[PDB]
Image (cartoon, rainbow over all chains, first blue to last red; front, side, top):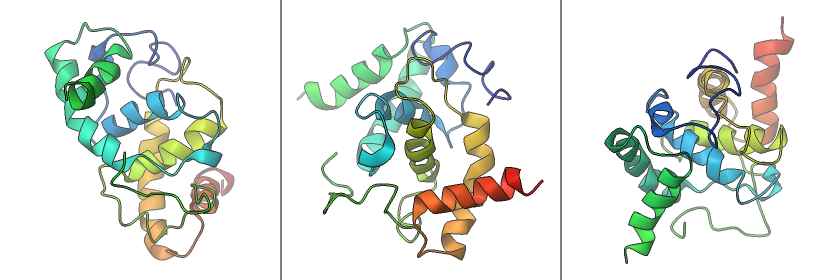
Length: 89
Length: 89
């Protein structure tokens, strides 16, 4: 859809900085991390059962972390926050 | 994530019911439509920028509709509200 963020397909989740994560409401920021990872772990929704606890644990990570660095690169924020959650051990 | 929706015989969004759409929090209710209709329109997130305005339009439809008809299959209910949104015109 076009009446959001900037435009349909012009600043996508593999082409723009973390400032574009703060354009989205709290209602759909968990969906913003959702789409970038959902499409990364299956091609079609025949294997979609949702990843609720993952999304709900990771929501307060990218939400803050994209305000910590608006100029941070695409996808590296979801990777870096998942690393802070698991890989930090 | 381990603490959520562990599968039995594979019961994805194409089998999963609206009664359990009420069990996930309001913060992540749009994430479920963002894991069905998100995948089916493409393959990968390389061109995605979220369907935010579409998801925000379609959320209050499915949120009420999953209480109206708890026993519906979720993939049929997202189609049902998309029809009532678009096809009704």
